[PDB]
Image (tube, coloured by chain):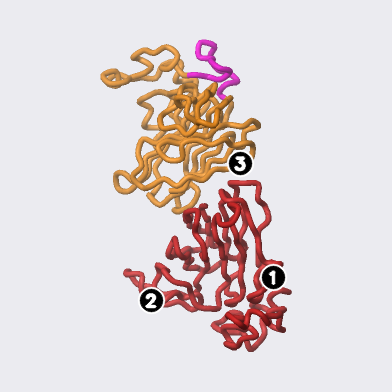
Chain colours: A orange, B red
Amino acid sequence: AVFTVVNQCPFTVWAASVPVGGGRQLNRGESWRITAPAGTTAARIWARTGCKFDASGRGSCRTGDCGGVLQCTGYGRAPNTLAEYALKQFNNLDFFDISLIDGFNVPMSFLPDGGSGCSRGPRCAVDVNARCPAELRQDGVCNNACPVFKKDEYCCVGSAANDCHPTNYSRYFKGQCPDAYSYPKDDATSTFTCPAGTNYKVVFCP
Amino acid sequence: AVFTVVNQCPFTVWAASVPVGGGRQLNRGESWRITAPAGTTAARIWARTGCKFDASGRGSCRTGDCGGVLQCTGYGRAPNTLAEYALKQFNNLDFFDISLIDGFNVPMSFLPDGGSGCSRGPRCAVDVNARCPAELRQDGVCNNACPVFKKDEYCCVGSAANDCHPTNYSRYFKGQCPDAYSYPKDDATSTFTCPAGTNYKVVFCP
């Protein structure tokens, strides 16, 4: 699949992509095109904000920082809006979603971009930071309940998935961006699928 | 670079791309995204009209047929509008053009599509078939003088390159589409460069 990442935000972001791409600085209007193999799972695409790096690839970002490295080898730190995907799994379908479980930093859209008749994709284009619950505000953006409070009801990791539920905090994210995952077990309204062979578009600030 | 190829013609084209890509059936409104690695040289992308192929990808095409296969491994037969490129050769520049030396079958555009601040690209969006010279009319479209007349003055191969000049036939195509190669030594007006890292868009009937 080819992923075109366009930064339309009025500020430079540092896009990141695991396990393909790594990272790259994008100014306004710049685009990046990534080619992911079919069968790539546990993949993420997000924007890092406020960064500084040296020639040796080390530095830090205010949001989304993936361990100092510019070319990220691993996931980034909350708060960051996640475009996430798994290519060509059951019945050779691709699976994708926008996740807000690790917060929000920039608005995003993850839509099909040809290669098939797939059209429907997730959008979280509102500025979730604008009306963020005070408890959750962090680094100028909105973080979510599990990164901020670190407890079972919000996080649902491992055994806690067995009773994972909406909370007042998940409901904020869900009201702002219906399409995106607002808490761990939000599968029924956030799973999108396209035929394998589809290409995709991720836009920071749709 | 990634090449996005889209069929905007009201008829199906079987797009072709050598040496990376092969071939793909694109109905009206479809697009194919090819990833050509840096270091590619002597490559071209074109459309074949009127093709009939079976489940093994074996059959024939009216224009641009590459050896009876869908999956092109070799260059195709004239008449066919050619998008030609070479990635990252001298001083990390990409080289590209549209050539009508092997005739014209569909209208074409070959533009930068981000990855750098490159904006200029060639296009031959005019219906060259409408005012085509009678003698060059072949296979329902307009072919050019070297493949029709097989003569040194039009083909300019080897020692004939030294005397290569415009003819009444190359001037027809250059009038129609000033950006494209009308004859072999038309380099001064038909060469475009973009920094390595640029991605491109080839559109059939822009």
Q: Amino acid at mark 1?
A: Cys
Q: Is residue A174 visible from the viewing direction of this image?
A: no
Q: Which residues are magenta?
A: A128-143
Residue A54 coordinates in the image, percent (x, y): 55, 28
How many numbered circles are shown?
3
* Residue lying at 55% horizontally and 78% vertically, measured from the top left: B79
Location of mark 3 (residue):
A30
Q: Which type of secondary structure does the marked residue at label 2 adopt?
A: strand
Instruction: Place residue A204 in its image quadrant.
Output: top right
Q: Is residue A132 magenta?
A: yes
Q: Quadrant of the C terminus of chain A?
A: top right
> Share a chain, discs 2 and 1?
yes
- Marks 2 & 3, CB-CB < 8 Å contact: no
Q: Amino acid at mark 2?
A: Gly
Location of mark 1 (residue):
B177
Judging from the image, mark 3 belongs to the subunit labelled: A
> Share a chain, discs 1 and 3?
no
* Residue lying at 72% horizontally and 84% vertically, measured from the top left: B168
Q: Which type of secondary structure does the marked residue at label 3 adopt?
A: loop
Q: Which type of secondary structure does the marked residue at label 1 adopt?
A: loop
Name the foreground residue: A98 vs A21. A21
Name the foreground residue: B51 vs A171. B51
Residue A171 coordinates in the image, percent (x, y): 46, 20
Q: Amino acid at mark 3?
A: Glu
Residue A154 coordinates in the image, percent (x, y): 38, 16
Judging from the image, mark 1 belongs to the subunit labelled: B
Location of mark 2 (residue):
B59
